[PDB]
Image (cartoon, coloured by chain):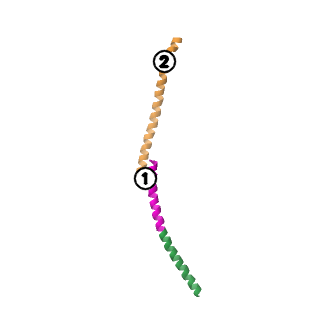
Chain colours: A orange, B green
C-alpha cells in the first residue's frame, strides 16, 4: 500500500490540473459571452440615442 | 458607452428645454404688458369717475 500510495500521489497531482482546466474553461466562456453581448448592446444604445 | 449615450440624450433634451423656455418667456412678457395696460386703464376710468 505504500507504493500504491506513491503512485496515487502522482495521479492526484494530475487530476488537480485537469480539474483546474475544466473549471477555468467554463468560467471564462460564460464570462466572455456575456461581456460580448453587453458590448453589442452598449454600442447599439449609443446609435439609438443619436 | 453609457456615458456617451447619456451625453447625446442630455444635449438633445437641453436644446429643446432651452427653446421652449425662451419662447414661453417671450409670451409671458407680452401677457404681462397687456395685463398692466388693462389694470392701469380700468384704474384710470375708476379714478376719473
Residue A25 badge: none
Chain ID at mark 2? A
At x 46%, y 27%, the residue is: A21
Q: Is residue B36 shown above or below A5?
A: below
Q: Which residues are magenta?
A: B1-24
Q: Is residue A41 shown above or below A3?
A: below
Q: Is residue B46 left or right of residue B25?
A: right
Instruction: Residue B17 in the image: state x and y as whole percent.
Output: 47, 61
- Principal SS element in the magenta part? helix
Q: In which quadrant of the rendered image does the N terminus of chain A lie?
A: top right
Instruction: Residue B28 in the image: state x and y as whole percent.
Output: 50, 71
Distance CA(mark 2)–CA(mark 1)? 59 Å
Instruction: Residue B32 in the image: state x and y as whole percent.
Output: 52, 74
Chain ID at mark 1? A
At x 50%, y 73%, the residue is: B31
Q: Residues within 10 Å of mark 1 (few under 14, many from 20)?
A: some
Circle 2 or circle 1, nearest the eye: 2
Q: Is residue A3 left or right of residue A46?
A: right
Q: Which residue is mark 2?
A: A10
Looking at the image, is mark 2 or mark 1 earlier in the sequence? 2
Q: In the rendered structure, does residue B10 fall within the stretch colored magenta?
A: yes
Element class at badge 1: helix
Residues tagged 2 and 1 counted as in contact (Cβ below 8 A): no
Q: How many marks?
A: 2
At x 51%, y 14%, the residue is: A6
Element class at badge 2: helix
Residue A49 badge: 1
Amino acid at each position: 500500500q505504500s507504493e500504491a500510495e506513491k503512485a496515487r500521489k502522482e495521479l492526484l497531482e494530475l487530476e488537480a490540473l485537469s480539474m483546474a482546466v475544466e473549471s477555468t474553461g467554463t468560467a471564462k466562456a460564460e464570462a466572455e459571452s456575456r461581456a460580448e453581448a453587453a458590448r453589442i448592446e452598449g454600442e447599439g444604445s449609443v446609435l439609438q440615442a443619436k | 458607452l453609457k456615458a456617451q449615450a447619456l451625453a447625446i440624450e442630455t444635449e438633445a433634451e437641453l436644446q429643446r428645454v432651452q427653446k421652449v423656455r425662451e419662447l414661453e418667456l417671450v409670451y409671458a412678457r407680452a401677457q404681462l404688458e397687456l395685463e398692466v395696460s388693462k389694470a392701469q386703464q380700468l384704474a384710470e376710468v375708476e379714478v376719473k369717475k
